Length: 213
Length: 212
Ligand SMILES: [Zn+2]
Ligand SMILES: [Zn+2]
Image 1 (cartoon, chains in turn orange, green):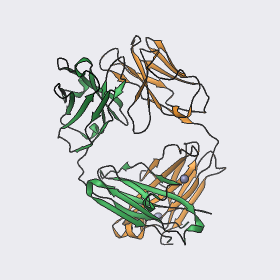
Image 2 (image 1 turned 120 degrees about the vertical axis):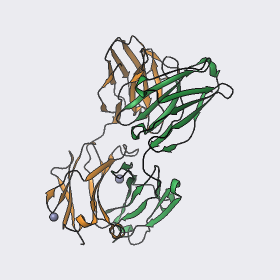
Image 3 (image 1 turned 180 degrees about the vertical axis):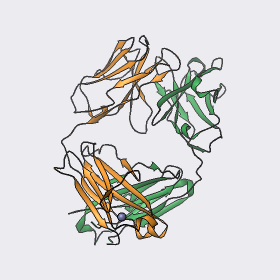
Image 4 (image 1 turned 60 degrees about the horizontal axis):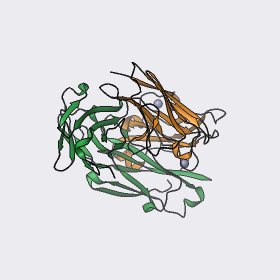
């Protein structure tokens, strides 16, 4: 089967910027390549067919080029509606195969997160488990390190993170990190802390609490 | 207007089969190939097969090892994809798509969840404001299947609200938090209630979140 490999996997750009996404096929696929745009919750939308032909109605700022193994999608001047994930596909040979996608996100100025920590609620504790939640609010860029410490000891393997899509108002991200323990384990320790490292912070910021106030 | 309309979300146990429909309209059904493609994190977009309704010939991606059957009813301009011997890795959004130098037209997608888990409504726990902006929220925990809906103050409160994507826990149940940032000065006067609905379990919960 033919592997379609896109480069880069993600990029940050501003409105008006020229954007270039490349796709390398593992073997020749002629010009039987299509490009798509996909937004969250929606099916992909066809942009380019037969490597270089805009599909009916697609704006002239989108163009495709290439043949054989090397393909390029260009957006000559990025518009607000163009922030999305883009995919290549070959239909030269079976099975048809797709690239992994390239996410085009909005560039903005660095913004440090506000950090908040939430102990487990008395309600949850009644029920045998303890979740501790660390919130990072409205930061940019997406890259952030969130480290849990319990009685000053670094944790591993007992937290999960979730991140929002870029905010439609300010183009920032928000992120939750949730530490889950048994109530029995939770009650064995005093200090719960999340430490956040981000480009916008001059040094890491720690939010912590003492169990049971 | 070419339209492809698929059947609704499905939840299946491993070993079961799922059959998804794709109702085609606005064109001559017998003259285009209709394909099936799926999407899930980690494998990405994956082509499954096609049917040509003119003669009901079908061809499949060999990777599915005969688990996929695509059929078409010419009398109703409807195509069907059946996927048998389901595994958790078959959890994905399934699309039908009409072919012509690529895929110009797609159905809306059908979510199929494959899990050993049983339907369960969420526990809803407050994330109390404690420590001029305060953060508060609700932890919506241990439900199956997706989705849940969360609102604040019956939808009156939308500014500063972040409802995080669900994460699948090792238990096979989902969890998420919804948070909102508000003026610290509102905490004594303004009531904050998260409204959580989980339709598969008939769960509708309103949890008042108060300072601790
Ligand atoms: Zn300890
Ligand atoms: Zn926020």
